[PDB]
Length: 10
Length: 49
Length: 49
Ligand SMILES: NS(=O)(=O)c1cc2c(cc1Cl)N[C@H]([C@H]1C[C@H]3C=C[C@@H]1C3)NS2(=O)=O
Image (cartoon, rainbow over all chains, first blue to last red; front, side):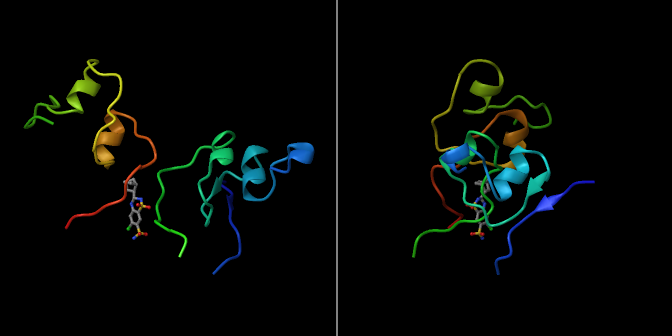
């Protein structure tokens, strides 16, 4: 499936 | 991308080396990122304040 | 576009029908225009006033 990368930032 | 080894790292490095398919994240669209990955039109407006 | 005929009249129609190469123009990036012609990233930010 599609992998969503992201950063931990509010 | 750290020139030292011209290795893109972080969220860009997951996209260039294919371990992640998309980066829906607060990522600033800049010139050096255009050379290896393609952005959509920018969803959020921001400026230095 | 034309009224249920899809003949684009405007600066889009000079692009979509092979007449012009590029529109360096005040042209809104919208959804339907994206499907028929390409856009760059925006050079001006604005809204309905
Ligand atoms: N509300 S906001 O400031 O987050 C915001 C910011 C922007 C929006 C829409 C909203 Cl709601 N749309 C534009 C987009 C719509 C089309 C025109 C320019 C791009 C493609 N990007 S933007 O100018 O970055």
